[PDB]
Length: 126
Length: 122
Length: 126
Length: 118
Image 1 (cartoon, rainbow over the protein chains, first blue to last red):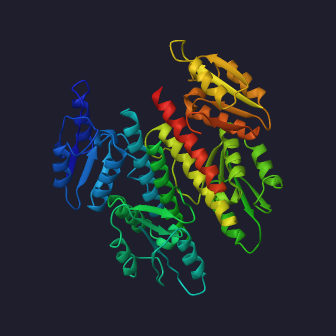
Image 2 (cartoon, one colour):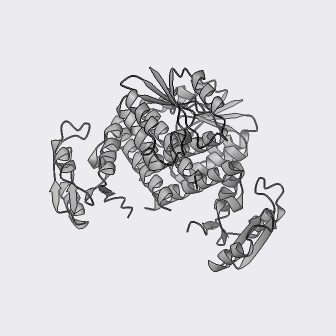
Image 3 (cartoon, rainbow over the protein chains, first blue to last red):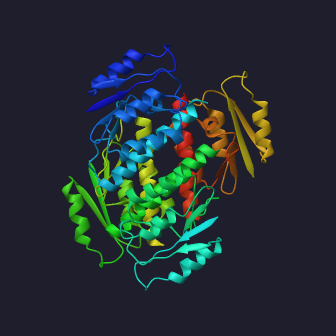
């Protein structure tokens, strides 16, 4: 199945765009939430969403910053899905998942990319 | 507390150098083994070391290549110690703004993990 | 135009393994050289290929270690193609232009990987 | 000889304190300019500073963003200094082979972040 997760710190942000952008990439069931991306511990909707998907499903976010503005927690979450055999996918970056160059180098590539975005997320909340 | 780990593919490699290298940085209980670092099933010795550490301890190795040559397993081994709050350190590359520094420390270990696998492939 | 370049330090290496590669990817004018890859200063044929290329042209090779086995020199050679506005594309590493879907992150990702390979090229040398 | 470079978009920002930071780490001759770091084409005082430095000298700034907010141009400048053999220090951020690669990467990250803000 294809699960999506949205998030907004306020209604100042365009959430209809965000939700529509998810459904564009085949978002089947979407878990919406309203909270600052400062931590997951206070985000139960995400905890439920992460617990919903099982071996085979796909996780969709509009961006890593929508997942969380916390390098430690995001990368920890990305590893959780990775271990749970659930492909994380980002709509803003619809190429990161395609690459068929070299299996080893493709894993390393994706890791660095997610790590870089995860950093900018926590660096930007400042 | 300190806990070291060593490994060699054969008895042709300088095993003593690695042991002394770990002893140098204050290794107390070193876990040695003779096995190819292609998988972790062959090395329960590592599992016994990962179950040895607690919190505030420090697991050390001469290099990432000695720890393992599998990118997916190595990074998983790093994340093992990460979530247990166990300080990981490399003898060859001892790296002792936190955000940028932690990102950099991770990124380098990822590179060392990758190169370790690419050496075996060729 | 597409220009190629090959290099070997010793015939111990299968030179033909390197020749047939460039010719496959539509190389019109290929150069060949036999020199130690520790320095670019003593490699004239390489420099002649760099003096022949122009704007809009494309420069191709087998790998980074064939452009030299010195980090500072290789990176200097790449930037020489940046400033001269010649697209560099390795055949060994099957990476495509536009890695993710954002020029900046693509710019960073391109440079990062080239720098990594240059390090591996010097790591094998030493 | 150590040379410095300070820049601001307007006098609204703290310029003097930036100059204090430069002269601290040993900024002898300092070039100061008032313009956005969007481009180097509209920054001739930065042209003077880059043409002044030479082999053995040193170029320093408060941060990379002061040097520019354009990944393409910022990376060219650092390489230009690498060609002139002029070490580029950063006030905000003060194994040899690794150290080279490790430094260059830090610059590229900071250079990237600096553009993303603009």
